[PDB]
Amino acid sequence: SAIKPDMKIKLRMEGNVNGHHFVIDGDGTGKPFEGKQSMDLEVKEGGPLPFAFDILTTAFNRVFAKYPDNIQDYFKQSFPKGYSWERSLTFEDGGICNARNDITMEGDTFYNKVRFYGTNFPANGPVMQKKTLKWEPSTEKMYVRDGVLTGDVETALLLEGNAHYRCDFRTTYKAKEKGVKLPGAHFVDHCIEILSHDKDYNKVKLYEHAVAHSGL
Image (cartoon, rainbow, N blue to C red; front, top):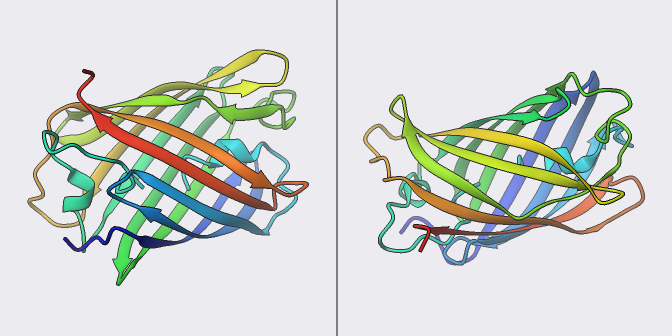
């Protein structure tokens, strides 16, 4: 295996939400074979972000997912050359985002070139008013669409006041190396959490646990 039990994570995200530009750095560690990662994120430009930090967090790597032997692990098989993903996030109030990550590996470190663009969030909505509390735990449905590994998530942000704000994800995943075999359909359970933050989320410690399974 190219991938060690303990790996480092380096990340830079650039993006723009509703016209607000930002650059955010990340440094972290994770356990690919346990499906666990954490990272410290720091907003470098555009802070204090005028929208809910939560919309960005799933853009901050399915190599950090515990795969059983009976499911093809496309992500671990993609290394050392790496892979890329592109994601559409569609929110119930018309907010729409497009995100990308190009993931490479240099030695013991995954590098992440992340881009995040959002638009059409209502000025009065929970994203632009910073009323989100967290993503709920989710299940991603992995399958092949038009010959491309695709993951769908139907999820929601919990808001203040016992309300949810629905979002549907579709992610396409592509290994750099020609010939990495597509997996059969399966599920990946996710739980992403902000473990700690400072006043305006200019510093955030983010955690994710993910486990692949067949629904049994």
